Image (cartoon, rainbow, N blue to C red):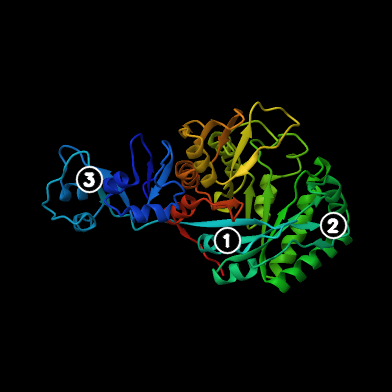
Amino acid sequence: GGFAQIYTVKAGDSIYSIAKQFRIDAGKIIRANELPNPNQLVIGQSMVIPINGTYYTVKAGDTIWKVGRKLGVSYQAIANANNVSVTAPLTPGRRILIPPSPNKRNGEFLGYVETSNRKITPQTEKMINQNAKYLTYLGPANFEVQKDGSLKAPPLNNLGSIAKENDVIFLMVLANIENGAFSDEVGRAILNNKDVQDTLLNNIVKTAKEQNFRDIHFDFEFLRPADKEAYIAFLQKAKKRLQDEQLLMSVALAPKTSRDQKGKWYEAHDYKAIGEIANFVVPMTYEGGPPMAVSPIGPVRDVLEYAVSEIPSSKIIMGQNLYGYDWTLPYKPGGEYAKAISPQRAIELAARYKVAIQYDNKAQAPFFRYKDEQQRTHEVWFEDARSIQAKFDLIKELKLRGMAYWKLGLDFPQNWLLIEDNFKITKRV
């Protein structure tokens, strides 16, 4: 980190002892974190302390003009930020505020809104409109591409307006989905018929002009390995067409860790070739499987380090989940699907069923188990300020373009606080 103050609730904490510790009003902490449980804080719960800069814990020898030299910060800035004389004594063990470095790097952020087969609410849209402040791209999932080259459009609700008013590029998500699943057959029909491709591109361009979509996002998945080359040829064809219309082109990539990795899901995506053609790409670095972290940082790193070896890092937007899952144990394949939940809901569950939140250092993700009123054990994996910050650190380390979020509308206040703390948000309109 180094740009945001992240605090993990400890035994005995109250919202007021935390407020005192950081010399900030409890109201600001509660509002910024939309705390569902301000009088029932959970051990292991993480929150962002809403200020510009971060805190330094005073040590035995410390002074202010000193801390100015030991860091790279104006001493008057430190003094003013803490409301003290420059020659003011410093009590060890207490925190002093250090103003933020002037230099945040730029980042592009993408938000998917799932509207297919749904009627999203005014409340959800209000939330999306708030999120859009922090976004570079946003659009509805999905336009379903048909075998004849026509498009089945999703509900657009108010997303075009939300995008426009927040200087966000309206993004057209194209998917080979039939009956609620990715279809290799739909992929085959389009990628092996040039007439259908022309019809498809006409429909894409027509739709883009009608709604002012300005990025065309191809999310073709589970293609036949046999159609690998055909996909590249189609994307080359699409790229020429879209550039002529001043449209951006982006492509979703199945998460891979090597060039000759086999499997119906992965073979048909040539990272290097697609990376050359697309303006940017999105490796799907997030997850009816068993309990585990949704996007464990080890495997995520492996996929992204491979991506960078094939594709300029400045073209890579990493995928990220805004949800966690609640599994009912014992887990059994074929049985019930885990319940998707917001991180706020996860906190509420830990509070309700009186358990601490744990943190997996290996996965860099929070989790806990709890027992419900039928004495069934649940296991919950979700996201918090710590886990998102770890991903942002990875973006900076690997010099990536930014992050793509599945899916907007979910309640996760700390994500948005941390984007602004860590990045200058790119606006392209």
| Badge 3 density bin: few <14, some 14–19, many ≥20, Cα 10 Å | few
Q: Amino acid at mark 3?
A: Lys
Query: On the image, numbered disc 2 is attached to which residue?
Result: 146
At a point 55% along the width and 62% down the height, the residue shown is: 132
Q: Which residue is mark 3?
A: 70
Which amino acid lies under the numbered mark 2 shown in the image of this protein? Answer: Gln
Circle 2: element type:
loop
Which of the pair 321/43 is nearer the observer? 43
Q: Which residue is mark 1?
A: 128
Picture residue at 51% right of the left edge, 43% below the top = 348
Q: Compare marks 2 and 1 and give the one earlier in the sequence.
A: 1
**Where's residue 404, x and y in %?**
59, 52
Report the side of 221 relative to 192 (left or right).
left
Q: Which mark is residue 427?
A: none
Residue 189: x %, y % from top left:
88, 52
x then y, percent, for residue 115: 70, 58
Q: Is residue 233 above or below residue 363?
A: below
Q: Secondary structure at mark 3?
A: helix
Cα separation between marks 3 and 1: 42 Å
